Amino acid sequence: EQLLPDLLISPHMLPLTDLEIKFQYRGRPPRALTISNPHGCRLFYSQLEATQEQVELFGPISLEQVRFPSPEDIPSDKQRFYTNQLLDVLDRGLILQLQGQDLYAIRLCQCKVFWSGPCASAHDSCPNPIQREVKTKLFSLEHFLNELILFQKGQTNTPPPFEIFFCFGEEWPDRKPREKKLITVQVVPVAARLLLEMFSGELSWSADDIRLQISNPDLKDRMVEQFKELHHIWQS
Amino acid sequence: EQLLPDLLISPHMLPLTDLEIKFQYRGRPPRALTISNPHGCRLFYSQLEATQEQVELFGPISLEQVRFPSPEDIPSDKQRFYTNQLLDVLDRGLILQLQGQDLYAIRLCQCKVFWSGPCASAHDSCPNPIQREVKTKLFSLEHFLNELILFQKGQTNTPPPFEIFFCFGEEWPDRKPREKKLITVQVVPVAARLLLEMFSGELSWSADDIRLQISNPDLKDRMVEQFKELHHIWQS
Image (cartoon, rainbow over all chains, first blue to last red; front, side, top):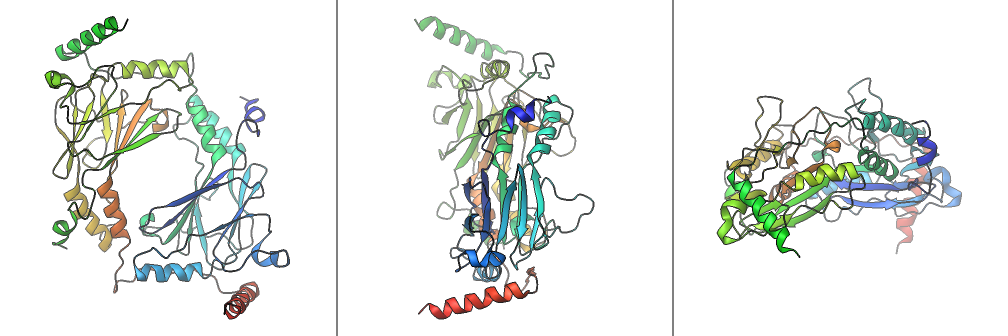
């Protein structure tokens, strides 16, 4: 299994820079896109553009510039009011940048950002805010693949996590349900999902863990089987 | 709130017969469709067709006839071998039928069928097989809406469940992860999802439960705000 990372973590094997980004406003259908910019992206809401002279404010111009969706079609005025208050403090944005195969956040926005994800701390139960201007590791593909290997061998029953969950402007994790959060964003490293699928679809020749569950045939089953036999005969 | 069911449970308000049906083979992308046949549907795999003279075997001809996807593109021969053994005993199928706004299963297939869902029993932890030829209630929209009402009022923190999960040919629920199940199907009553969205997007005028989380502005925030002010000025 030691050859696997070198074999698989490669542009000819995986889309190493692809992130799927799903925006969700409370009570609306989600809106998703995929970016493959190798510098990463910046999620933000602004009338102003990132420029070279203002990188301190808005980050590097090479990031994929991904705007939060208009809240216009939020039917509740009260909800759209709160939502606009948050979007008003999202001008500087949340940078998501790949460093090798690790994904990092850099929060620039005045809006607070809270998150859940593969590298998030698991020592308490309270909210998990992202500190402004502090490079925060969200996900490691190296570690993901190590864990994937143990899962596939059946050494763990838990599939390794890859999805990163952000809540903008309200605390998370929380007692309260995600359905009631005004603004959330889910981010998937597509290479990780692909790798989980790939490994899930590889079984052992030796360790046959599979016990099919099939009733004994009743007379109805028997009639069906005979009809299948006759149909096979008739073909030809 | 007593007027709500009469108001909402109506064809002019909701798609009362729409089910989304998602097929998933281990390690493959899922494959989904939506049916809106008011009789319901039959999930099956067969070279034979439902006919009038064989309703005992294959169910009523009015059901939407939904075939499991070919397992051809499953890359593991061993996996596709087990998968074909299950598909070979799925000729008679699993009927999903609406009775008013309740959804019921009738298993005809020789393959065993196990499930998780809104009406599933919660007294033990073991597998939950569907009994062949026994009308099995999966979901109640009436009850869903009652629960939705309590959620929206904040009387419960848990959103009411609507998704029904079937595993064909292997035990469920189980120690083992769903990612390793050969054949699963997820079924959503679309009216229920719509209703959850609708209710989630209705807030109170009085019970304002929302505390926005926004840092104090630093000098960078202040410069951004001034640039926004200048841009608003410049517009016009």
